[PDB]
Amino acid sequence: VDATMEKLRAQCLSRGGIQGLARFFRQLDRDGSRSLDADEFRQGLAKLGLVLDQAEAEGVCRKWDRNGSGTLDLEEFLRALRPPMSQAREAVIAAAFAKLDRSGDGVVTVDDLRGVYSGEWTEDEVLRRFLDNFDSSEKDGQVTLAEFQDYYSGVSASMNTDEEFVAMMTSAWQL
Amino acid sequence: SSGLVPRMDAVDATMEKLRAARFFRQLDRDGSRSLDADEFRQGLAKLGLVLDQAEAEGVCRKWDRNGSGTLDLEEFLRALRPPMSQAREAVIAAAFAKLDRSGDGVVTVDDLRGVYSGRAHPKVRSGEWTEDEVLRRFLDNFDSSEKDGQVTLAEFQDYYSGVSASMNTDEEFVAMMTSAWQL
Ligand SMILES: [Ca+2]
Ligand SMILES: [Ca+2]
Ligand SMILES: [Ca+2]
Ligand SMILES: [Ca+2]
Ligand SMILES: [Ca+2]
Ligand SMILES: [Ca+2]
Ligand SMILES: [Ca+2]
Ligand SMILES: [Ca+2]
Ligand SMILES: [Ca+2]
Image (cartoon, rainbow over all chains, first blue to last red; front, side, top):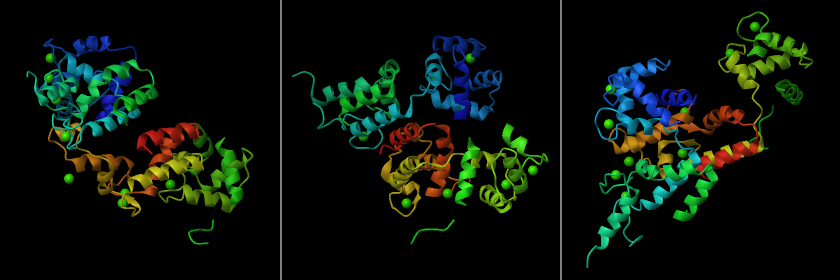
């Protein structure tokens, strides 16, 4: 399934880079509804020699559907086809996430930031504003690993080598 | 001395030289889609690499994983892999040593739990997978074809034989591994 999802990109790499993904997105969207259903997604991949069944399709849509619409919009689809980051880059992030997550339950919260960072604006209200920086656009007081990972998708994309990324992360977080 | 097993040196020489599908099919004189000890023997002579009868039989016996008495494509492809240098063997063992927390010779989910947290994983955050299930999933990749939550050094080595063969220089391979397992 992930192998099928990688063959898609390998195939997209034959010309298509992210502006091309929107172009392909809209050719997948048969009804033009501006989102992809598991059905539309499946028939589109079939046209490319990639085969998975409906339950597999819903599964892929389930994974990338970030707002529980049961469907893939342009943003989610673009995030789906982003070439995954190399493992070394992923490892330093992982590493820095562990640091940040004092409590080590799997998510970073205002409480994890207590003791590590610090009339109007109070204490953890400031701490909350810090948490927000790394959080998604819709702040909910929790930072996942996936979210933390997005926060750095920008600079990572800019930086051409793992060592540039690795060196930066190492110093930022004193790993 | 203890730990040593007797093994044939002249076979190692002939086997090296050889290393340096199209080829398999050439050698498969009788089109059986597998190599007799006898055919392998004749093929190598036709190429100027000399092996007697038992030496050729010895090589089939040791690469014929499934015990068909013969070498098929998968088995032949494996045999031609270059021997693993001290350096590559060293990073593999260091990575295995790291994973095997209990130090009982096998890497299990229980080992892994002391090395990695699986909690931050997206499939755990959605409620669909447990930490141990992500950890088991990770373990399976290194496991033999029959998954049993146990990965032995043999199995670990077998897993990396293929990957190793993919990279040209010891240094690429050593650095890869050092970044993969953070040693
Ligand atoms: Ca649609
Ligand atoms: Ca959606
Ligand atoms: Ca936490
Ligand atoms: Ca969040
Ligand atoms: Ca034959
Ligand atoms: Ca065989
Ligand atoms: Ca163990
Ligand atoms: Ca547990
Ligand atoms: Ca096993």
